[PDB]
Amino acid sequence: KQIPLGIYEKALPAGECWLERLQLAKTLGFDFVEMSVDETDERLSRLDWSREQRLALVNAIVETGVRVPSMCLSAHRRFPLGSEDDAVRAQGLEIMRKAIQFAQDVGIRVIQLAGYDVYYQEANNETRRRFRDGLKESVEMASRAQVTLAMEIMDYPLMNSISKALGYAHYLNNPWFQLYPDIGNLSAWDNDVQMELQAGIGHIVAVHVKDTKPGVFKNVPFGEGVVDFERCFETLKQSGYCGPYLIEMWSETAEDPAAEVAKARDWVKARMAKAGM
Amino acid sequence: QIPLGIYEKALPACWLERLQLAKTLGFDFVEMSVDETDERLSRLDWSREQRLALVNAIVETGVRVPSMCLSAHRRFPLGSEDDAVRAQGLEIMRKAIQFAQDVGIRVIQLAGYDVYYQEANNETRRRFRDGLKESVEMASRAQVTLAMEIMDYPLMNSISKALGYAHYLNNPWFQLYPDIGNLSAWDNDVQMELQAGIGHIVAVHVKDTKPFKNVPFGEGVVDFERCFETLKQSGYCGPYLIEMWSETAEDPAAEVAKARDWVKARMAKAGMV
């Protein structure tokens, strides 16, 4: 009767002591934190951490009891796998290799992939093909290492539904490729959200919890968007989902991040409770 | 790369020393054993410091421990009609999952015995099914892969039987860990099976058998080149583990060196380099 609840790294204060980060998450009542490896040189430099830095993270996790089971790899927005610039695409694949090695090192269960063929450039048939082939190569790296890659449902039309991610799953036909729906992103298009959630059961390994509006996929306060949280929670519970939920928010920049996080936590937990969890 | 590993029990009976040896023998990883012995079970009760010591050694040598063979369920089976015994099985399952989380183990290989030292029946099968479901719920929360071995036991003696369970459970954290020796020691269409299971195969045990254990490589009925070419042509890109018990052979290191070269030659013949 346990429901693992997590908080996005970027909801908490920015300081790079992981022991304190994990200790804070613990006091706020979270079971885990999801690491961000984003477009910043600073967070990307984590992939070049020394052995001692990697083992310090493991130590902090074992000592606090607060896991880092997942990594959001949004760095691919900057170095996408579908880039027509072969130099950019090579660094995207290199980032993928290092993220997988990083996950092996520190015991990260799931690398959440960004479903962008290109983000800053215009998409075409070539970027789609290169994204597909880059994704296949990534999944082969993941197969060797035995590390799960889970495709996020995106703020972007290529990967804006569970159905589209399932299309990729059928193509790859690999146990290390799974689904990480974001119920906010899933609700901000023209999807039959409740059917999508049910359809993805069997491949859903984690769920991002955030609110959205059409065209607005970031920093929409809980309750001010279009997400039907209770219905999504009901669908997932009734279909047999037993995995974690991660509250995605960016309260890093707030006057009091911990206070913002605590409010969102209680808000989300109330909707889970209503849905029988 | 073709990731190649060695079973824990193929090397003589500390982890730093074990991993450094495996490194010098050319192996990318070691598969840990959590068997019926109180000795290896006690690992599930390791202190935080003992767990951290193993991680330290893994990071230092570059030799991974990505999988655990959980054969302890032979002693505390999930289908046991004795509630106390079944409860011990489920507690072992919980502790094995927690141990894999702590130490960064990727895959726990499950034993597909409803019961082993007792005769099976509808009730043991029913109990095992429910225990499996509970185990998979634990694994879903922890995000740890449980991979069913294809067994020297009728309930799970083919990839098909494990796929049946996979369809029942419909959960991303339940996968397949075929043993090509076990697969070949019954009346299966083994190449059909290997192909059917692609999409769920996360690891492969490499051993020879007769219609089960310590059969020298090339002396049993397994067609290694055929199994390797089916796996390669089907798109398998995961690890291979050489299963042997040369811990107590005349010269353990010399035995595994020979087995490694023998296996790699069979792989080469199938187009794997």
Image (spheres, coloured by chain):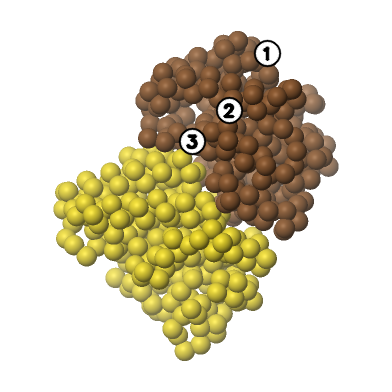
Chain colours: A brown, B yellow
- The answer as to whether the residues below labels 3 and 2 share one chain is yes
Q: Is residue B232 left or right of residue A138?
A: left
Q: Chain of mark 1?
A: A
Residue nearer the viewer, B57 or A145: B57
Most distant residue in the bottom direction: B250
- The answer as to whether the residues below labels 3 and 1 share one chain is yes
Relative to A74, residue A264 above or below = above
Relative to B272, residue A107 above or below = above
Q: Is residue B12 left or right of residue B53?
A: left
Measured as percent of width and height from the top left, residue B238 is found at 55, 55
Q: At 39% across and 65% down in the image, what residue appears?
A: B41
**Callout 1 amino acid:** Gly
Residue nearer the viewer, A72 or A80: A72
Disc 1 target residue: A215
What numbered label is drawn on residue B8? none
* Mark 1: few/some/many CA within 10 Å (<14, 14-19, 20+): few
Disc 2 target residue: A247
**Callout 2 amino acid:** Ile
Q: At 19% across and 55% down in the image, what residue appears?
A: B82
Relative to B41, residue A21 above or below = above
Measured as percent of width and height from the top left, residue A24 is found at 63, 37
* Mark 3: few/some/many CA within 10 Å (<14, 14-19, 20+): some
Q: At 36% across and 74% down in the image, what residue appears?
A: B213
Measured as percent of width and height from the top left, residue B93 is found at 38, 53
Disc 3 target residue: A4
Q: Is the residue under label 1 in contact with that under label 3 (CB below 8 Å)?
A: no
- Callout 2: helix, strand or loop? strand
Q: Chain of mark 2?
A: A
Q: Is residue B21 left or right of residue A129?
A: left
Residue nearer the viewer, A207 or B39: B39
